[PDB]
Length: 74
Length: 110
Figure (cartoon, chains in turn purple, orange):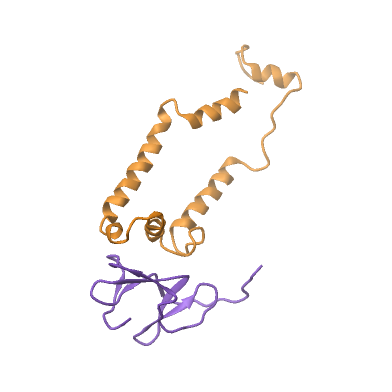
């Protein structure tokens, strides 16, 4: 069995609206803040990776309580 | 030990050597375990709900059946209202002659 031995506390987000009412959500992980731009992180190992479409489930519209950031493009 | 009633069966059984010992864990502890599991499922960190907010978990579970995501987050208020209504109905349904109570009184009476 896989087993962690150390931990780190970070601020996460389950999704965000990035364009004209579109939604993105992580496949298995979270979105984290790093200097005014968001990156994906796996849910069992802390490693910032750039925003891709292979780790993101697209949405036709985002939820009302998702974070708002028109700056992120995809 | 101290009483004025004689038609009870449990006292006669206990005096005749037949006795039902309490379990090693009290039901208060098991209720605390179920409460802890439910709270960890609901509040962050979402341990029992695969690390995601509960409403979004309901949204994704409904979407996986075939429901599109456009109508899901535009019906979130009525989805939560329907979930609360289902919880209240399943709460109030135990007052009638339900089937779960049929099993519980079945094992007790057996």
